[PDB]
Length: 225
Ligand SMILES: Nc1ncnc2c1ncn2[C@@H]1O[C@H](CSCC[C@H](N)C(=O)O)[C@@H](O)[C@H]1O
Image (cartoon, rainbow, N blue to C red; front, side, top):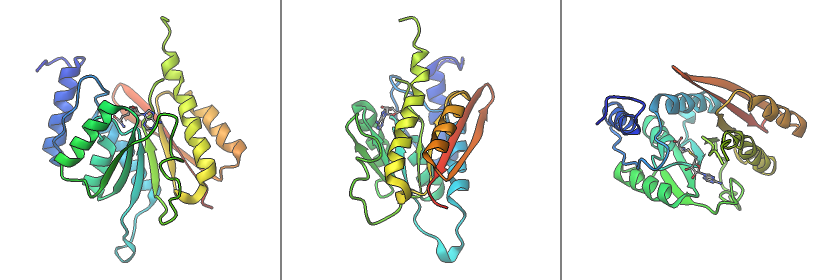
């Protein structure tokens, strides 16, 4: 395995070795798809913890969340379910990621806590949660996809993705307690904040995740007063 951390073979080896050593999670992921890095994925898991609230022992419940675009790694549910005993609905549109995510759930014996679903690509939350009338989800989380010489247009597409989540949230309302998404540039934040302000979303928060050279923002919102 390469010693140079610019090489994806080295990043993948480090991520997979970290997950085994610290958590006892063994994952298999293809170099064809985004290789998650663990420290940033953990920051977000902990931020979800802060958002959904600490429970006294007498009102402990199974926490339930939705990870939109779960990846080949199925990283956020594996971590959420392993650290915290959270249940996840985890969605994917990509066949290769779906196959891999399922395999990673099974191989870490977590099929009881994580349900991986392949949705259709024009769908987001509303189709996955349609005629759910029995429980309220505590959260959704999302690390969004980036959809000539200038696909930094790809990076800009994160805005339209989040707006779709905002769109679904406006109909689902209190069916989930906290909607959230990680953002790739701090200049995605101001327009999204203004979009929630003008739709009258009552509760909005945000935070920073820093891993050395790399900086991410996450935004979250709720229709609960
Ligand atoms: N409408 C949609 N519903 C569910 N997943 C989607 C989607 N649109 C794109 N995706 C998936 O979202 C993923 C974003 S990349 C994030 C992967 C993983 N959560 C991680 O943090 O490493 C991709 O695998 C892409 O296939």
